[PDB]
Image (cartoon, coloured by chain):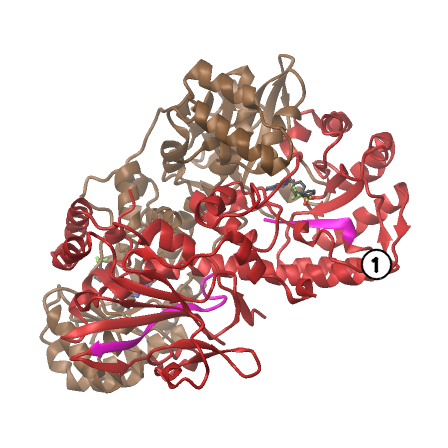
Chain colours: A brown, B red
Amino acid sequence: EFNILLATDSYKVTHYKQYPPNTSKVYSYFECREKKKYEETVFYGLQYILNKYLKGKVVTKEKIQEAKDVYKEHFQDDVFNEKGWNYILEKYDGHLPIEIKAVPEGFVIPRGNVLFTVENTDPECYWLTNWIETILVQSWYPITVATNFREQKKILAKYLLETSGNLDGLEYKLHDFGYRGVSSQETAGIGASAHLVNFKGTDTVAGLALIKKYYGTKDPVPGYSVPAAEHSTITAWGKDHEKDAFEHIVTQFSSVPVSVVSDSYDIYNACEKIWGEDLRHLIVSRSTQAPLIIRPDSGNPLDTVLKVLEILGKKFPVTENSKGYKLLPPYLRVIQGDGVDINTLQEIVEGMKQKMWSIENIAFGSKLTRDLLNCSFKCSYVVTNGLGINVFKDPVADPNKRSKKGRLSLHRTPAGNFVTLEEGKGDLEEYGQDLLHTVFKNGKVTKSYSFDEIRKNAQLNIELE
Amino acid sequence: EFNILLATDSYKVTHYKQYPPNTSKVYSYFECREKKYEETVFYGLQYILNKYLKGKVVTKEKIQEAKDVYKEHFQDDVFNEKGWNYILEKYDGHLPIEIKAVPEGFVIPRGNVLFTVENTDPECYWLTNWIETILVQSWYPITVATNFREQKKILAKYLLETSGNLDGLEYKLHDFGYRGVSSQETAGIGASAHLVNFKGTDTVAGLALIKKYYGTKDPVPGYSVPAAEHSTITAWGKDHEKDAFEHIVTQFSSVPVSVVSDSYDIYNACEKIWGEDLRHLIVSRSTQAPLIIRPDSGNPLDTVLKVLEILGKKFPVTENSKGYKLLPPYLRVIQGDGVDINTLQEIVEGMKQKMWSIENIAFGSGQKLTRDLLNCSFKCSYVVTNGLGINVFKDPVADPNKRSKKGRLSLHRTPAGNFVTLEEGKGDLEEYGQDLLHTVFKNGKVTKSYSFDEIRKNAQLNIELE
Ligand SMILES: O=C(NCc1ccc(S(=O)(=O)c2cccc(C(F)(F)F)c2)cc1)c1cnc2n[nH]cc2c1
Ligand SMILES: O=C(NCc1ccc(S(=O)(=O)c2cccc(C(F)(F)F)c2)cc1)c1cnc2n[nH]cc2c1
């Protein structure tokens, strides 16, 4: 079973002995620190952490003893605030005396703004605020995944709109292929849920169950897939029988969309001779609701996509849409799922546009770090001897690492943007309502968002228009 | 509860229908495909076998669950309910799969077979690649273990050159990465991979994982000591940094303590606060209880060098037998900002050039490694259809680097004592001695395992082996 007493950075076990004596409050905040482009971030994923790890009776006698035993060996010393944890157990039935206030999930907020704050609700637990920094800071991952996919969606939207005149199918243009490529089963679920804030096509099944458990959708599921081959289902037929594999597979899935990886031996031969001649009669007969989706999976991503389109355009009837761009027949599409990151995605759609190919023709299949958006948790306010003091770091050699001072609040500006007020200036009430809401207090999740609301919050402007 | 029927890439749910008719065997393998990082540490499969693959992993409820989910996910009935029911009924939900692997901790050159997977029942030909997704995640502990071993080689080289020995090497790179990984589970797995190489960690999650899945003779595989963070310094107020420092070193007067010193001005903190105002509290400390000063901002190399020069002028420095400068034993430095394998190299070389021993410094690790770094990859190499075995492979025209191995594979020692992978069942010709892979999983049971102590021994540096 998960033990919150064992879910912090080791050194934090020793911090209760280091704060100023007579400190009754430690108040901390999380931001995606501005850096002297990723100018706005999607706040997403805190609700998962709150429910899975922070809520309810998270302290027990057994958990305290377990931690005591582990830390004794780990530190070769008895340092461990057994009394402090006992107090939470006895006084609060093992519920964390913490209040967390956060911007609503799905909100798109410029860099350098307070996203959530954390403080102890009982003076005895001044040490607890930063104990849980480690676990809360891992919110950097769903925030950065949600943000990065939103930025990729902006690129796709721009090019789809320009080449087609509309945004039809946009939410299925970037399919999550990343399950095998992440570091763990837990990460797979979290990352997939963040992808699904932006898109609806996924092969990372783990994301569905996480969304259902922690967030919820009106629809039975938040994400979808369709049949497709992998190299093993093609190569198993033998090198001389690729055509036989293709035929079997498209015939098995004759009435649903089917994607078929076509580069096992020679992608260009597969497109021109196998799909484009030998099996063409099985493709042109397919429904608009059940296209063949050809998947190249190797070579230079841009060069290969363009050459594949060029080949298919000469073997199948191409039309020109009202924007002047070339469009494959509705029973035939292409998906590129090799080497697609935000930079290469841009390169491909731009390259397609230059060659007069509509983005309607293509879909894509998809490391990020905590430093990308400078996700950071810092103490900004403490009360010592009954006096509040505004605290901060400001390293001489790096002004980019300066932190905010005092009690914080987030507000709409008169022009409708965002501003973070420091030093308790929100109390002056010159800027309307604080946009941070209490989401956790004393062991209870106090405000929750559905996955539907989060998706709405995270919409692109071009979608709103 | 984890459900293996829901732990694969969605498209794999449809593959049972796509293999050639009458296929009785699918056989696949994992390698770190050949294209720095010429040898990889094989580590982490044992966790996956025990946590996810062994025992009764199929139940009626899990089958119904997957059926319901996939019906909505695919907007159609495509899920192989019958195939999973067969495993439930015939094998009491244990997977009819055999896995053979190189021993955990082994250091093996790129492009060798590391593990193989095949079905042991003809009805379950589709099962081999169902579990590709789960098994391929072994890329992460392999890559973490490998990258940290490569960092250890750099540290060993420079520590040996500047001090004449390797004392303290296993405490020279401390894991600071708990907050910077993607999940609690990843934290435990990644920390365990770090601990294959080192013994100092702040990622507590790693200890319990090692204890549960691997085991050590010692109570714990990794250690830490007290240290400050910016909040425990800055909480005292901007004008009271000295008061914070004094309190902390006094609270931890008889154990090692690390104090971050860059909250406002690292150079002033070192020269005036530590080096003058509080010097009397430092020079009185035991060799077993040093102050470890931690800069945490600025150019990592430039900052380390300036911090050492400052301390060198305020504290008595000696010259060791190799001619390098050494701080007194009650005083050390740790650099935990911006340290990846490249910057680690730049710092130790920069120190060497300025005649500072590597004894003076430790590093904190806390750059993202991906599955592409070592080209970790799982591919089908052999199938049996209509009773005939066939050697299979991909070989994409535009990328020869993605060509996969053919046929049944085995791992062997060459006459010179190196590794070679034999393809096309050639291992059976008995010209290269015994297959070095061991069966580690068969029919729902883990059949061979390794303690964490043995894994560490397997992963040792040559320089450590002397
Ligand atoms: O092909 C794969 N999965 C199936 C798949 C995914 C995505 C598409 S798609 O063309 O985006 C598409 C088409 C129609 C409906 C949907 C829908 F509405 F359902 F989203 C998605 C079609 C098929 C695949 C391929 N390679 C992989 N490597 N690692 C994981 C992988 C997964
Ligand atoms: O200082 C931190 N943790 C405590 C710590 C770690 C490492 C050292 S060390 O100097 O390598 C050292 C010294 C003596 C014994 C050990 C031993 F034998 F115990 F390993 C380690 C001393 C203290 C720390 C600092 N910043 C962090 N950011 N994110 C996580 C962080 C952890």
Dividing the image into four quarters, tell me where ligand 1 lies. Answer: bottom left
Whether residue B159 sits left or right of residue A224 in the image: it is right
Q: Which residue is mark 1?
A: B354
Q: Quadrant of residue B324?
A: bottom right
Q: Quadrant of residue A201?
A: bottom left
Name the residue located 30 percent from the left edge and 43 percent from the top edge.
Answer: A210
In front of the other: B234 or B122: B122
> Bounds of the magenta span?
B359-384
The quadrant of the picture occupied by the C terminus of chain B is: bottom right
In front of the other: B56 or B428: B428
Looking at the picture, how far across and down is residue A124, in whole percent?
A: 55, 16
Looking at the picture, how far across and down is residue B124, in whole percent?
A: 20, 65
Whether residue B84 sits left or right of residue B283 in the image: it is left
In the image, residue A254 sits, relative to residue B302, either above or below, namely below
In the image, residue A170 sits, relative to residue A464, either above or below, namely below
Looking at the picture, how far across and down is residue A258, in whole percent?
A: 18, 67
Name the residue located 30 percent from the left edge and 59 percent from the top edge.
Answer: A175
Is disc 1's CB within 8 Å of ligand 2? no
The kind of residue on which mark 1 rests is Lys
Magenta-colored stretch includes residue B116: no
Name the residue located 72 percent from the left edge and 26 percent from the top edge.
Answer: B251
Q: Is residue A392 visible?
A: no
Q: Residues within 10 Å of mark 1 (few under 14, many from 20)?
A: some
In front of the other: B314 or B82: B82
Magenta-colored stretch includes residue B361: yes
Element under disc 1: loop
Looking at the picture, how far across and down is residue B447, in whole percent?
A: 36, 59
Q: Residue furthest top?
A: A386
Figure label count: 1
